[PDB]
Amino acid sequence: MTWNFHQYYTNRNDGLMGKLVLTDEEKNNLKALRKIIRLRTRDVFEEAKGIAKAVKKSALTFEIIQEKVSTTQIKHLSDSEQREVAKLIYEMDDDARDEFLGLTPRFWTFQYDTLNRPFQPGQEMNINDGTYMPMPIFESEPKIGHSLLILLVDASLKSLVAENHGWKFEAKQTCGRIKIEAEKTHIDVPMYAIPDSENVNLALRERKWINSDPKIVEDWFNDSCIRIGKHLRKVCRFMKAWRDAQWDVGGPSSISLMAATVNILDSVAHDASDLGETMKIIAKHLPSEFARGVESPDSTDEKPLFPPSYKHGPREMDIMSKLERLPEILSSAESADSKSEALKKINMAFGNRVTNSELIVL
Image (cartoon, rainbow, N blue to C red; front, side, top):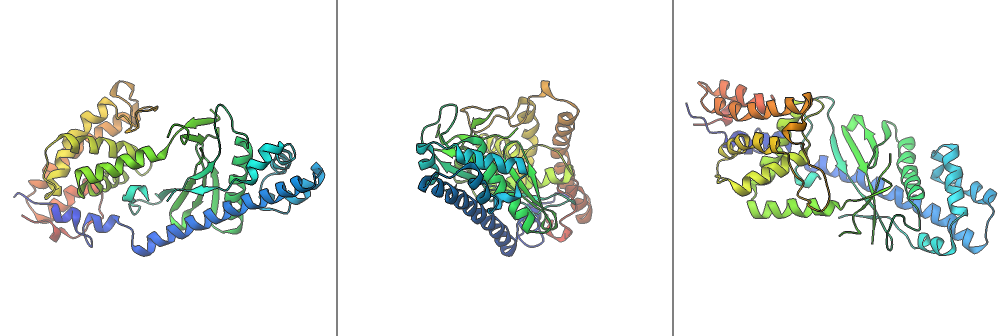
C-alpha cells in the first residue's frame, strides 16, 4: 500500500509541524525572558558607567570606587571579581574611560524560525541572544577590555539568577548561559565587539577574541529559504526533530543538518508539494553529505560543521549509522501494510509524537 505522508508532516494541529511549532503564547514568553535579560545588562552597564562618570568628575580612590561597586549588581560576583572591576575602573585611561562612557550594549533584531518544542525529558529549547559592543578598531585588543566586558555581562546574568528562583548560571566557552529547567529553556548570551570582518569579533571565555559574525549564517539561511521555498524551514524542523528523537543528548548540530539539507535541496530535483517525497530525497542524500564532512556556509574562517568520515569516532559512527537507517525507515513506512503500522514505522524516525494515524493517506 503506497502511503502518502504529506499530511503527517505538514498538518499544523495533529501532524509533526503541529507537534513542533511553539504556540504564540510560548514564543512570547521566550521573548519576555530575552527582554528581561536585555534590560538587566543594559542597566548593569549603566551602573558601571555611573561609577566611571564619578571617577571622571572627581578622580576617586580605589577605596571609594569599590564602595560603589558593592552597591551595584556586581555585588553578585565573587570578592576577587568585584576587586577586578573596581581596579579596571580605577585604571581606565582618560580616553578609554571616555569610550566606556559612550558605550551601550546593543542587541540584534528563534533558531532561524525553526525552534522545535522539546521532545524527550529533559531536553530544552536553546535560545541565543548576542550582546554587541560597538567599539572602534580592533587589532589584538580593544581599549575597554575583554575581561571588564565579560565581568559586566557575567554580573547581569548572575544578578538575574540570584533574583529568580529556578534560574542557574553556567559559563560556556563562547557565552554565558542562564538555565531555567522548569521552563525547559537555556538562554546563551555570547558577546561580540563590533565596529563584516571587524564585526566578527566574539569574546571567548576559556583565544581571547575570534572572528565570528552570526550574520553570515543568518543571512545565508534566509537567502536559502527564499531561494528554495517555504518547505526548507519545514524539512529543517523535521531533521532537527529526528535528531531529538534519535538522541536524548548528542547527535549532529542543527546547523550541520541545515547546511547539508540546503545543499541537497539546491542540487537535487524534488517535489515540494509532497513533503514525504522530499524528506525521502533528503534522507537518501544525507549520509554522503555527512561522510564528506559538512562545511559551514561561512567560507571565511571555520572548521567543518560535522567532521569527515576518516576522523569519526564511536559517536560519529553512531550518527552515520542512524542517518543511513533514515531513508530505509522512510521507505518501509511508505510500503507499510496498515495505516497504524505506517505511523509506527515513520515514528521510528521522528519519535512517537504524532499519534493520529488518520493523517496518513493513500
